[PDB]
Amino acid sequence: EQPELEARVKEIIEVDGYQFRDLNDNGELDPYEDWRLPTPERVADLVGQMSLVEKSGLMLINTLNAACDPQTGEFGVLPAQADNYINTQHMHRFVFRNVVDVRAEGVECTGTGTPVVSPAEAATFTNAVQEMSEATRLGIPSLFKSNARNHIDPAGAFSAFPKEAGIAAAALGEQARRTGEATTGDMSVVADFADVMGEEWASIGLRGMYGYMADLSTEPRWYRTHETFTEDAYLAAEIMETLVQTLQGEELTDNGLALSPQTRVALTLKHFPGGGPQELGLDPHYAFGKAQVYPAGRFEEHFLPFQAAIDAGVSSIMPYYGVPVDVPVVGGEPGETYPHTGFAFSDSIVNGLLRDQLGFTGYVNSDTGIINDRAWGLEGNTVPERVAAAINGGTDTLSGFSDVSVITDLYEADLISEERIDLAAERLLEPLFDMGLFENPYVDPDVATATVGADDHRAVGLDLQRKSLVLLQNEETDEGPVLPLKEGGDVYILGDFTEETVESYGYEVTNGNVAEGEERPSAAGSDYVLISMTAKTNAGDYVSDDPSLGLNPDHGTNPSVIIGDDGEPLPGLDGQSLWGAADVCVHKEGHEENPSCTDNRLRFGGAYPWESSILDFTGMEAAESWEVVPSLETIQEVMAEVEDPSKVILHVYFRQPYVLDEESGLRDAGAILAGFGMTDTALMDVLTGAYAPQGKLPFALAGTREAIIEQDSDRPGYDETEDGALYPFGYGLTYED
Ligand SMILES: O=C(O)[C@H]1O[C@@H](O)[C@H](O)[C@@H](O)[C@@H]1O
Ligand SMILES: [Zn+2]
Ligand SMILES: [Zn+2]
Ligand SMILES: [Zn+2]
Ligand SMILES: [Zn+2]
Ligand SMILES: [Zn+2]
Ligand SMILES: [Zn+2]
Ligand SMILES: [Zn+2]
Ligand SMILES: [Zn+2]
Ligand SMILES: [Zn+2]
Ligand SMILES: [Zn+2]
Ligand SMILES: [Zn+2]
Ligand SMILES: [Zn+2]
Ligand SMILES: [Zn+2]
Ligand SMILES: [Zn+2]
Ligand SMILES: [Zn+2]
Ligand SMILES: [Zn+2]
Ligand SMILES: [Zn+2]
Ligand SMILES: [Zn+2]
Ligand SMILES: [Zn+2]
């Protein structure tokens, strides 16, 4: 019956033999403090006593990182803006972005940066914010969200798993190992991962997530394919279902939300209705990439994973920045299309599709910076006008917006009704009640130390690392298949292999990784060449209003067209404009005089927009804003030096679905693997045969740039291209001894 309580500011009262937190400090048991009552009655009572500004503060969510004190040496103290956000803006939702890890030897507090914090220091920080929250007039608790933390970057003290697509590759591979088929996957793999994450996140007082991503990698030119699970909507739907059930629980409320005190992490699924199908792969963080296009008419396949998570009870939904171009309204009158504005401003999307058509009963969380930076389709509108349009469109909380006074001002100007603010307040407050946070919002920092990165948790991650690896090619030689490796030999390594780790398996290693000013030993005479390679963007020089770049006629024109709902094309988006002409620094269609460029330095990722279709390794080596690592030139020298290329093992990190073009010579390697993030001993354990590979690709790979240029950005695979796929979805070899 009686749930545990903890209070550091307010007092505990007991009534009818039960104890309660007196959060308004009146000395009596209000219904919102009365945990015996159903949540709607607790919310109604709480919303009844809030001032307008306290209600409007709930509609903001902003970065609140732990800081360090240069004079005490303590890490995990409150930042400067904590007092403002909690006490002046009345916020109770925050994004925690610090790396959680143990700092080296010698690290002292200094610099503008975001300090690294241990698990115990992270818990101390979030407790302190909860302490400051309880100290407010009604002592409403706070909720921290974060992006993903448990993935190897090819994190910190959290237990390390492969990237999202590696988890899907492992799930498909274990289905095929049990059934013979690779369709929707073995979801015990996903549940095992989610179980470790939920336990570790909750132990530091991190009870929400910006994620996971249900977006589909149907457009290989989209730089965010690196954080998608799959291109296939039905596998994605099965994964989102399992993530909600495991992270939120299977216990549903009467509203149909999987929210209980058993909820370890409440998910804010992103990015609705699906960020995958970007025109030319250009991303809507950037002005030139506002458009999402659906040439194969698959808009409904893309919100199918969201559908599945909504039914499993997911807490929260984040719309993407994108603009849906000419999309028929689901369940609407004939000839109706969705507005050509960003998703969070469209009542048709957030209230119509998400709530009315799909039945979502939770709250809606904007993506970060839609108001000031990415108010797509609202370029001429003011900031207050943009706030009202997102809130009235169905968006309940604004990520990256700080200023509660703008919402109160919009109320006094009758641009947002108080009935709408009450509705947002209800949706935002209910999960905090249902998750037990009004009763006890604190955590034990020392239990975090014993939980984050536990040995058994790390073991689960290691298993999935080994099961994510996909064997794509393993050529038969006179002495048998290239893989697994034989015992002993001379091994040449290139790329991110640790020499002593490879030596430890009983090989003599020659390291081709030399600095730019030293000569590289030849690979001649090696029994094996281990190359670990990938490609990266190097687009930090991009400037939208620079005639050398964004305004350079030699870079061509942006083919993307978006006709505004007023009848005029969006700036720089008429299909004839220079790439940089869509940036507000160029068009200046707002209220405000020389606006900064939003696209400068492409700081979120992605190549130069004129280079977004160069996904082949040969093209990428020559491209201005792509880089092959190690260089394709060095790789090609090395493969010639060994003379017999079947002695070369390529381990490739397909950050995007890169194209192994025949001109590049990479297909002459004896073995090719796709890796999604592993320790060196996990990969050496598979290469040397202690374990056999079993992963299967959760997206198809193409063989030509033409297939890249021809495929439909909203359709999976390459079956409609002339050249087709090099490797299809669900493909992957093993050792057959
Ligand atoms: O972390 C954030 O605030 C968000 O940043 C935005 O740029 C991304 O679109 C979203 O996926 C992140 O969750
Ligand atoms: Zn007191
Ligand atoms: Zn009573
Ligand atoms: Zn009270
Ligand atoms: Zn105030
Ligand atoms: Zn408040
Ligand atoms: Zn990445
Ligand atoms: Zn199911
Ligand atoms: Zn786009
Ligand atoms: Zn009035
Ligand atoms: Zn303790
Ligand atoms: Zn454990
Ligand atoms: Zn054989
Ligand atoms: Zn030696
Ligand atoms: Zn020219
Ligand atoms: Zn150029
Ligand atoms: Zn003005
Ligand atoms: Zn050379
Ligand atoms: Zn496609
Ligand atoms: Zn051709």
Image: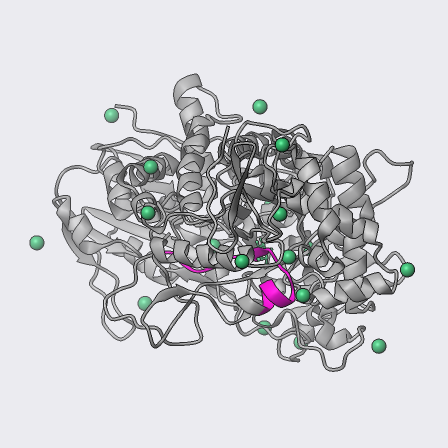
Percent position of residue 113, x then y? 43, 71
Number of labelled discs? 0
Percent position of residue 445, x then y? 36, 51
Q: Ligand 13, what quadrant?
A: top left
Q: Would you say residue 94 sits in the magenta stretch? A: yes
Q: Would you say residue 651 sits in the magenta stretch? A: no
* Residue nearest the viewer, comparing 582 with 559: 582
Q: Residue at x 75, y 48 (%)?
A: 48
Q: Residue at x 72, y 48 (%)?
A: 47
Percent position of residue 261, x then y? 52, 35
Colouring scheme, one of rainbow, by chain, secondary structure, one colour: one colour
Q: Is residue 559 visible?
A: no
Q: Quadrant of residue 253?
A: top right
Magenta stretch bounds: 84-100
* Residue nearest the viewer, comparing 294 with 447: 447
Q: Quadrant of residue 432?
A: top right
Percent position of residue 583, x then y? 71, 70
Q: Residue at x 83, y 40 (%)?
A: 328
* Residue nearest the viewer, comparing 88 with 710: 88
Residue 616 vs residue 550: left or right?
left
Q: Where 292 sits versus 698, above or below? A: below
The image quadrant where one finds the C terminus is top left
Q: Is residue 552 visible?
A: yes
* Residue nearest the viewer, comparing 200 with 493: 200
Residue 613 vs residue 462: left or right?
right
Q: Where 413 sits versus 258, above or below? A: below
Residue 456 vs residue 659: left or right?
left
